[PDB]
Length: 127
Length: 127
Length: 127
Length: 127
Image (cartoon, rainbow over all chains, first blue to last red):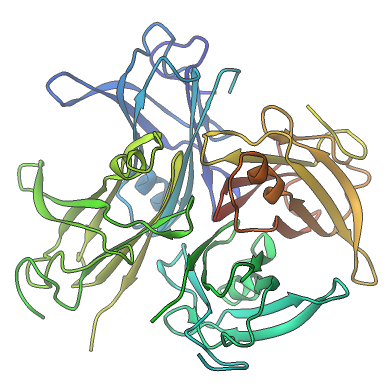
């Protein structure tokens, strides 16, 4: 695996899949932002998906406080490397982190050239 | 509302999209079956999607009685003709229809070589 | 093909579906932005989906010049009004448009409380 | 975890997610069929998803020969337990297993009351 800014009990994980080739989406850049008080997006963590299409160790429990986050997936670069013309500039996921709910957040993204789907799996357990 | 093999107030429509090309999926074969009294699948209607990736005129309100129906979409032929060998043999949609009176059903499918999604839009008639 | 805030040969359309109720998503707020010369998002058009879950009349072929556009769909308001508290704050679609002449763009979105999918259908004009 | 008929290097795994609640789909029945020479479907393996929404140990490498398989997911029961009216009778995935391609097959299914998506991840490595 690759990583981000601080690694611990992995409160946040990203998984990206390729719907064209039926495989993990490898070496895809992912940037995480936290919404700041001035309503701007502050860089928070970043990395590249591993050979199993996952990105772990982006943050730690102490750091992952309640707030608004944005996960940006560089889908355009991914398709370009394959010699395929994509529609989207990138894929963005914006969500609120709340302490009330379950503690691990898994963001999954399924990519096609002209379409994507994203889903959140929120649990108590592990990934 | 007519009666037979045509289109009533089109009680059943199919719409198919291609997530690789960002266009309607044209000339896709569709076969519809109804579960008979003896529990086997009987042929009900068939057609091919048009240039807009839609299929209308499959049945009439009179012919479309209460029952369990299967919509089979020939995805494999579609991809092979494009030079791609896909994962699935076909996409199948199975549902109970009209069990509380006549409804209008739109079955939508979004295709990728290794993934598909299907959604139903159900409307309670009148004109 | 007109000119301004209306609908040319409707160059940009949005369609939103609800995967929980099996119906169009009605009264969903949509905001469109264009990336300005200084790299910031400028307001371009806004509307609400109709009873068929579509939004037409956002722009004209003349106003819809080459550029990077963001379509923001207010999913959170939609679900909350239904008594559900959803995962995402909104769904965002970002793309380059018209970089090889005028095209017609349909942006479709399928909504679930913890997941959404978006697809683009691009057509090369004429009438 | 739960299991199927013979457990080994897990050539076939099933993962099911709930798009309404953003969680694993637990205790969902899954039946696997292999297409027989008479063109009928022979029961092959079955089980219920575990608390992480997965089903492993359905088969072994020796048994998983090339052929046509069907994976049936009992989605209707799942929604009914939640007190939600679903559209589909069940979700079906039909595919050919070939020795040429990568060796592990992961079938994932994302469920909503009126929609589902399925994706195949085929790899050399592990799950």
